[PDB]
Image (cartoon, rainbow over all chains, first blue to last red; front, side, top):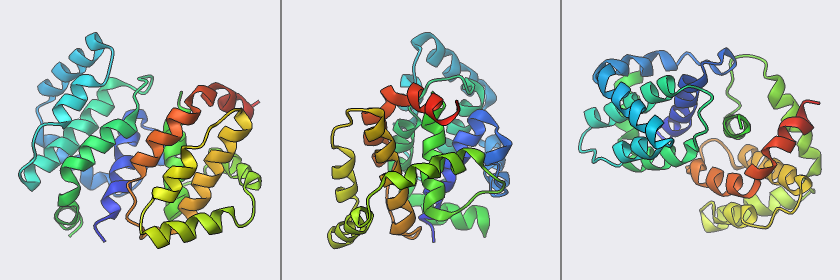
Length: 119
Length: 117
């Protein structure tokens, strides 16, 4: 339906953060392929800034960057996921805040993302 | 602490019934359902549909939480609304999570204990 991307992406990103098998889902396989869109180096830099800032501020700044196409969208999804993976599960982050910004920027592309990844 | 991600996953699950394996944490969280009065959810769902929005849910979530009892009840009402509103509902759940958590995050420790003691 397209609107299903919201719940899926929330589940995906949180799963990337703690890698708890309980919350594994086949559909994540396709989403992980997006990892190649972002440089592992940019992620490391972002993680460092989050760590010295002791907060999600830098992640939120990156999420607030404009998105003009579906490729930019995939990128933001990929950076959120890679950051969730490298920041670690002990990280006390109010994920709903990142989700709010993320979706504010990519929701409009939900339908095209669904067909592009599951079509 | 991990209550945050747990509750997000629990509420989304209550909405679409999607999971791959048995979830013992979800079973324990569902026990909270008994705290919700009959009709309460029904009325909430009704108002959400009349307004075509999550406003009524947000209103309910903005009410004061004075004790762990209230915090548990707010979790249950959110879960029950999620289940009865239907998965097709285009709700931006992250906004309800924001209100829910600012209202009950202090009780995360008690909940973490109250659930697994």
